[PDB]
Image (cartoon, coloured by chain):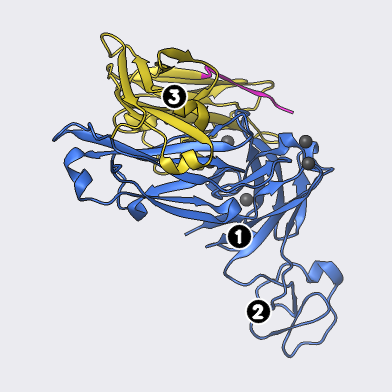
Amino acid sequence: EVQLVESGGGLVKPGGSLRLSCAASGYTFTDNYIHWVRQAPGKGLEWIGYINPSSAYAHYNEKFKTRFTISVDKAGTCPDGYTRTNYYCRRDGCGSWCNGAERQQPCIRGPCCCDLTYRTGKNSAYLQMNSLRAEDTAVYYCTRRYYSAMPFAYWGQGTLVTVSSASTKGPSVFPLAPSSKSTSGGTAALGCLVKDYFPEPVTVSWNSGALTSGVHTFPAVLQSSGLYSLSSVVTVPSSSLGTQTYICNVNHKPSNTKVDKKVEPKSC
Amino acid sequence: DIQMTQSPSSLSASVGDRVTITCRASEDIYSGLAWYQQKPGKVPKLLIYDSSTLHTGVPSRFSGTGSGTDYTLTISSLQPEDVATYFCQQNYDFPLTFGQGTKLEIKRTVAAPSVFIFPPSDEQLKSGTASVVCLLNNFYPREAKVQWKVDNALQSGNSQESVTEQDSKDSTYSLSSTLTLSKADYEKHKVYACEVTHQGLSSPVTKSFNRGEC
Ligand SMILES: [Cl-]
Ligand SMILES: [Cl-]
Ligand SMILES: [Cl-]
Ligand SMILES: [Cl-]
Ligand SMILES: [Cl-]
């Protein structure tokens, strides 16, 4: 499948720099432009720029030209039966001259000279951003058109960039234990309180993903301390509370904090 | 730049209904307009391009019309899984620019919350802080009032609330409210109560616990 897989996002202090990456696979890398788009909380999507990996030409939204740079890996491969030279390729058993960029650019069928190419696999574009400020906090996407003259149809998953002076902090995970008054033969609720972390995001699953029905994981709230907190709950049969095990799997990758929290009725 | 203005900012409609979202460009974009659907945490999905052409996999109850500066996305036979933000994007001109989005809610029948209160854990109390949590589960409409009371004193300014995305199948919401107190204050009081007002409840409902009770 066509995939764009982003990485590199995280916390950065005002004035700092950060390079994000978009690893593209599943199609000829030079066939399509890679664009960068961002989405700040509330604000609508904002187009940043694109790069054409065939030519490495980049075009920017004026708003970002001073601070942001879009790039791609350098290509360094010559097809089978070709040998690399200074900056292009040479066909084995050819020697005649080749007219500069004109004849060292596209690889016509099987010429005497052909441009350096990417290997199939993952090839990456990048977004370098410096002099970041608070209003650059956002989810940053890479994306490409379905085809020339068609809109963005393939999107990277998004990577969060947080521009703040606050320090990284891992969460504490506390039980929301099922009530001793839970209705006999009825429905009980329990959960996990994921408290005091920074920056976003945290993810929560239950029973390593085996438990999905009845789960609600709430949006985080930013507390007056400048730290986030959120809750995840699930409703289950009251009768299962003595037997079935319930574990919330919390992952705060920004602090390298993974926690499995067993949640059970409190003893007296 | 071409500024895209989307209207309304939100709308609410029943399953089977027909709704329209409008996008207006600050200049003629000659039908170079795309529509996307996006759910929270998920990537945009391309619905329509060239103002009226449906993309692969998109049901035909989505339809785009318009010309000049003024375009419309129409969703017929609204379905519960259509809860999402919808936005337009012009492709006529760089810089590419997007509308600000329209959030879509499904109107269903009133459903009262089930309410649950949770005391602070002993592990947290070692930290010097106490969090009390009130859960309102699977209710509609979204409007709901939570009042915290500690030995019959109303608490104000020391709680925060969060609401889930409207459920894509049953069209309900759920809500968490967290009351935060010092451990010292928690230990000086006995009765902790969450009182919930909601259209589906005939009268407000209170869930309470006594500190230290098993
Ligand atoms: Cl393209
Ligand atoms: Cl700043
Ligand atoms: Cl700083
Ligand atoms: Cl989060
Ligand atoms: Cl279009």
Residues indicated by labels 3 and 2 sit on the same polypeptide chain: no
The residues bearing labels 3 and 2 have C-alpha atoms spaced at a distance of 51 Å
Query: Could you tell me if the residues under marks 3 and 2 are in contact, i.e. CB atoms within 8 Å?
Result: no
Q: Which chain is blue?
A: A
Q: Residue A231 versus residue A78: which sits nearer the camera? A: A231
Q: Is residue A236 magenta?
A: no
Left or right, A57 with reference to A243 = right
For residue A24, which quarter of the picture?
A: bottom right
Q: Residue furthest left?
A: A185
Q: Nearer the viewer, residue B192 or B168?
A: B192
Q: For chain B, what colour was chosen? A: yellow
Q: Is residue A225 left or right of residue B132?
A: right
Image height check: is A229 above or below B136? Answer: below
**SS for dot 2:** loop
Percent position (x, y) of residue A47? Answer: 68, 39
Mark 2 or 1, nearer chain start: 1
Disc 3/disc 1 C-alpha distance (Å): 33 Å
Q: Nearer the viewer, mark 2 or mark 1?
A: 1
Residue B104 — which label?
A: 3
The residue drawn where x is 66% and y is 52% is: A33
Q: Chain of mark 1?
A: A
Which of the 4 quarters of the picture holds residue A266?
A: top left
* Residue A79 disc label: 2
- Residue A23 marker: 1
Q: Magenta stretch: give its range.
A: B1-9
The answer to which of A4 and A134 lies nearer the viewer is A134
Which three-letter amino acid code belongs to the residue tagged 1?
A: Ala
